[PDB]
Image (cartoon, grey):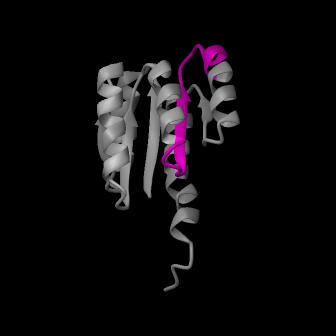
Amino acid sequence: MKILILINTNNDELIKKIKKEVENQGYQVRDVNDSDELKKEMKKLAEEKNFEKILIKSNDKQLLKEMLELISKLGYKVFLLLADQDENELEEFKRKIESQGYEVRKVTDDEEALKIVREFMQKAGSLEHHHHHH
């Protein structure tokens, strides 16, 4: 069971800020560049069954959809955030992912994105709270 925060923003510098958020929370920042790279990193999602927090950076929304369709074989809670000024195509893209049963959040703005990343931590709090008493 691994907690993935998938980030697709055309603001590639906003990813660096979203990194600062997840680095303080101890997420390992991965990045998908190509389809060959995709299936390599999907093998890591298949191999690592141990509990780990990962930030998936990919600014190509096609790699995302195909990734999540292969994650459907693994079966875990994945988070997704879409930040770009063409929120039109993001609103169309979230429609597939939300129907696939994956967490997807459509935004545009810098701090509007960052707040949802800080939320993905407290959303993953429900994953933590399964028979885990203190």
Please report the bounds of the magenta region as a residue range: 72-90
Could you tell me which residue is drawn at 52 percent across and 58 percent down? 124
Up the image or down, 125 lies above or below 68; here it is below
Q: Residue at x 52, y 52 (%)?
A: 76
Query: Is 76 inside the magenta-drawn segment?
Result: yes
Q: Nearer the viewer, residue 6 or 51?
A: 51
Q: Pinpoint residue 9: horizontal percent, then vertical percent.
A: 46, 25
Q: Is residue 134 above or below residue 130?
A: below
The number of numbered badges drawn on the structure is: 0
Residue nearest the viewer, comparing 74 with 79: 74
- Going 65% across and 36% down the picture, which residue do you hit? 100
For the point 53% across and 27% down, the residue is 65
- Is 93 on the left-hand or right-hand side of 121? right
Location of residue 25 in the rendering, given as x and y in whole percent from the top left corner: 36, 56
Q: Looking at the image, which residue sits at the far front?
A: 73
State left or right for residue 29 relative to residue 8: left
| Left or right: residue 22 compared with residue 9 | left
Q: Does the magenta-highlighted stretch encompass residue 64?
A: no
- Residue 20 shows in this picture: no
**Residue 72 at x, y = what percent?**
54, 41
From the viewer's perspective, is residue 34 above or below residue 113? Answer: above
| Residue at the outermost bottom position | 134
Quadrant location, the N terminus: bottom left
Is residue 10 or residue 54 the one in the foreground?
54
Query: Is residue 110 at all visible to an observer of this figure?
Result: yes
Q: What x and y, as percent, mark residue 75? A: 53, 50
